[PDB]
Image (tube, coloured by chain):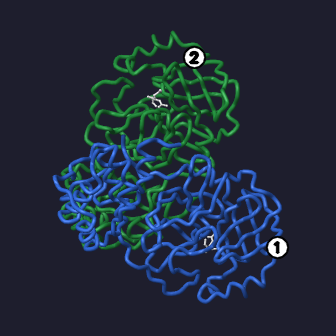
Chain colours: A green, B blue
Amino acid sequence: SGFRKMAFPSGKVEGCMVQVTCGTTTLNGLWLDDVVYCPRHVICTSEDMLNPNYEDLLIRKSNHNFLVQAGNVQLRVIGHSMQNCVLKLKVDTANPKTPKYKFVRIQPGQTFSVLACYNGSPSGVYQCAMRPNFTIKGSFLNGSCGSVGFNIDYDCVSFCYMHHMELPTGVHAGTDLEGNFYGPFVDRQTAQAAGTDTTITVNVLAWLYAAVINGDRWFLNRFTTTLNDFNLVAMKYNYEPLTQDHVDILGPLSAQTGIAVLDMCASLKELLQNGMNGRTILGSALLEDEFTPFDVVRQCSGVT
Amino acid sequence: SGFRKMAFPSGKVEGCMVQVTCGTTTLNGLWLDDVVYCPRHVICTSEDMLNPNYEDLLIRKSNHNFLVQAGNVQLRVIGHSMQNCVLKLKVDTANPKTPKYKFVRIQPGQTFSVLACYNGSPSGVYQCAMRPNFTIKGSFLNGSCGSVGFNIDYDCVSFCYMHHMELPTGVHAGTDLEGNFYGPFVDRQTAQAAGTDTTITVNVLAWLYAAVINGDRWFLNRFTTTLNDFNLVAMKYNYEPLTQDHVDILGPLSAQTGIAVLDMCASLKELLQNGMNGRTILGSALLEDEFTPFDVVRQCSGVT
Ligand SMILES: *C(=C)CNC(=O)[C@H](CC(N)=O)NC(C)=O
Ligand SMILES: *C(=C)CNC(=O)[C@H](CC(N)=O)NC(C)=O
């Protein structure tokens, strides 16, 4: 029993973190096989970041200008290329700790673990969600660029995020491991405002299911609703619309608890309209939306 | 910027987890050098747990009755002893991934990372606090016994917790790595009720400091207080008394922010008396107490 915001064990990713230095910029890289992946703004000064022409800046860089350090041992860079907003540094040594991996581009509402790193060294691990506005609310200080987000399926690390940017509002933006930003963000120090940070409805409902499973039941009401009626309330509270796809995904939690998904929607509707009245659910005074239905099943079943 | 409930990177501890089986009971063990540490109730049936005599149960067990599996390779047990509520299984092979380590017994209010494990395999990592009533609010399913809590100082793992027990209220109890329970708990399936779960005041104040540092300032008021006046309010709200030792520990966060500790106490006093009025601090609708002053400095400074 108990339900915690839980990250994947980070060891497999710790084994991939390196330091990348280009001139006076140092950030983190991800060493998989004989390639080190890092944000392309490693080639920039803070001055460059105001208006960088990356192709032009890269012309001035050779293999020997990229200093890659894995622990306290230097890797030899034998090639470099830009893919979208990442650099791929080819090194002469395959990372011996390379886990089975994939590169995945996640959808908004999907959760992942971040291994916060500085100078190629892990500082901490925490659980994030891709917000509906394609930001993440992370903990990223100067030097954290190139820290990665990931999911693990048994022995396979799916890398979904690399950290690039803090917006002036202090929310975070980054790329998948092909270098494509999530959302409309660019790797430039300019005015970039996030859209509406809506609540990930399917994730709130999953977490209400987790609550019932762990004995927090006070919010369960006598009502049901429809998707259309629920969605009217959801829109009013800046919640994402719930689709039949979301209802289908919640099916196993519905089955386990014997609470129809639309009944849990009606409970959620009353919590939106009535508030918590100073009560908590799983030790929270607000409705948690950074657990996916898959997260709740995993944590409630003990998957390793 | 951003402030997250952050666990230590778990790789160093992942490298220590093994499966221990005795008859039909399987749980987790911690393999450090040539010793595997696990809860002594590995020798119990669920029937035994109602009223176990551990010394008597252990007489019936030989080295070959303890099955220790590290990955999918069996370790040879060459000795066993009971220390308090843990078994120490001497094995013929030193764990080659043994990190620098220490065993520490933490105080209430101290935070630590848990690596939740099943069948010797890590499922997740999360951040916990030793509650003032010597429980932790964890996420622990059947099979999680022997999962450990730890802090890391650069390269040295300080193990502070091993999981033994879920109380009927669904909060958790366990031992240090010498086998001594935190609090009054015993490894028996009997009526064990927790005392008052008070709020860790020094940790709330640390987190209010983290909030100011990350730009959440709305709760900062025009007032100051004294320790004695604050403590009267703290008692009324089931907050731990604040001591001058706590004020001293908050000194560096006081210095960084320029907010006197007693001024932040007066802000906290108003939040207790007035509530949040539907506002959030660092994305929380309640006052967070599972960040120590050391945690806040570490996360705000980027220690690796
Ligand atoms: C993202 C991490 C960009 N890096 C930085 O701004 C700092 C400053 C620098 N000298 O590169 N890097 C570190 C390691 O603090
Ligand atoms: C604490 C983990 C005690 N272990 C258990 O109760 C279960 C049941 C068993 N067969 O040992 N262990 C597991 C691995 O589920």
When the figure is inspected, residue B181 is found, relative to residue B201, above or below; the finding is below
Is residue A37 in view? yes
Q: Which mark is residue B64?
A: 1
Amino acid type, label 1: His
At x 67% / y 30%, what residue is drawn?
Answer: A73
Decide which of A217, B218 is in the foreground and name it: B218
Q: Separation of disc 1 and disc 2 at Cα?
A: 58 Å
At x 63% / y 23%, what residue is drawn?
Answer: A90
When the figure is inspected, residue A280 is found, relative to residue B258, above or below; the finding is below
Decide which of B184, B4 is in the foreground and name it: B184
* Chain letter of the residue carrying label 1: B
* Chain letter of the residue carrying label 2: A
Amino acid type, label 2: Asn
Query: Mark 2 sits on what residue?
Result: A65
Which quadrant is the N terminus of chain B positioned in?
Answer: top left
**Helix or strand or loop: what does disc 2 sit on?**
helix
